[PDB]
Image (tube, each protein chain N blue to C red):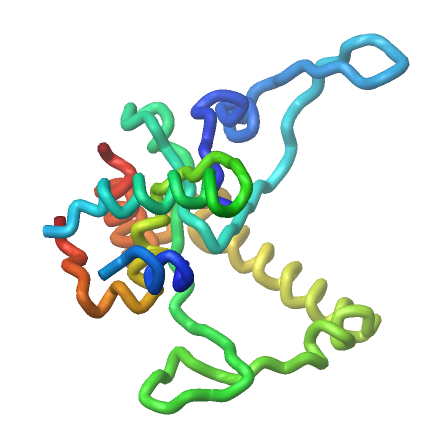
Length: 139
Length: 56
């Protein structure tokens, strides 16, 4: 179902400061937030606010390709599913090792160029689509 | 959706359609909230889309 963002309980999820919370059966604790966050849904989200403080963060994207059992023509974005990607090809240790190698290589690439900050690589597709998204959700 | 379209559906702001659907669901088929938001897109996924004006 479509999910509504509170515009709260989200600044702590994104701002690189500190945040406190309490666990069952003991006291309250505070800790840094060293996390990379990602979310997805087939239903559009809800952003009630419009202020720059909330829209400075966040990066929206819209996937174009689609997989169906029958690769219907006249649609390059339409292709056929591979059930071997889900039933297997994930628990295979060699695939995981290769993915780890790809990830570490991409980390090194991001380290050497664009300095270390991620708000330096230009992706006009992502900025344009995020601008279009911000034009929507604006009652 | 198709059941209601067949039974009772004969700028298309969709307010009348949304209220008909929500009331219908909350009656003929159980009782529950009917957030719309994308319910317009769901209706435009049905047969009523052909005889529908997407623009308000």
